[PDB]
Length: 48
Length: 49
Ligand SMILES: *[C@@H]1O[C@H](CO)[C@@H](O[C@@H]2O[C@H](CO)[C@@H](O)[C@H](O)[C@H]2NC(C)=O)[C@H](O)[C@H]1NC(C)=O
Image (cartoon, rainbow over the protein chains, first blue to last red):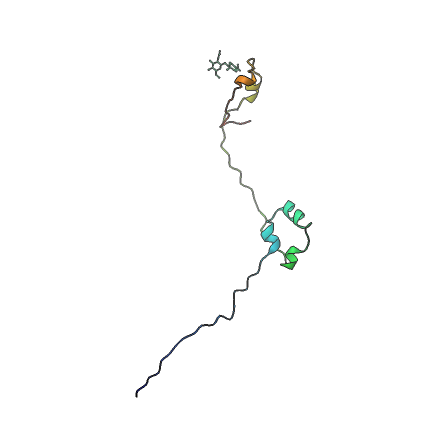
């Protein structure tokens, strides 16, 4: 016999933080031997 | 591109001066050589060698 109007809310996730990883700098710091050894592995960092 | 790092511009060197010597040669060249059954031990700390 009588009515009103209610209000709801809804959140839908759309985006996400764009995470970029420096594979070379993460696996090896500023050291020469580490980079020299990592250069003999392949393209793992490239694939990442 | 690949990462980089700021190159150092100086060098810090801090050490305690005016310290005695360890004198390990006087301990190794003693006239009292023990045996493996009663081997001896001397601790060297706070000295220069
Ligand atoms: C060589 O060994 C002797 C015998 O262990 C040392 O003489 C003893 O030295 C200690 C100190 O490290 C003293 O407390 C003892 O009284 C000494 N015993 C003695 C004199 O019979 C001696 O110091 C060692 N080093 C040298 C350079 O001789």
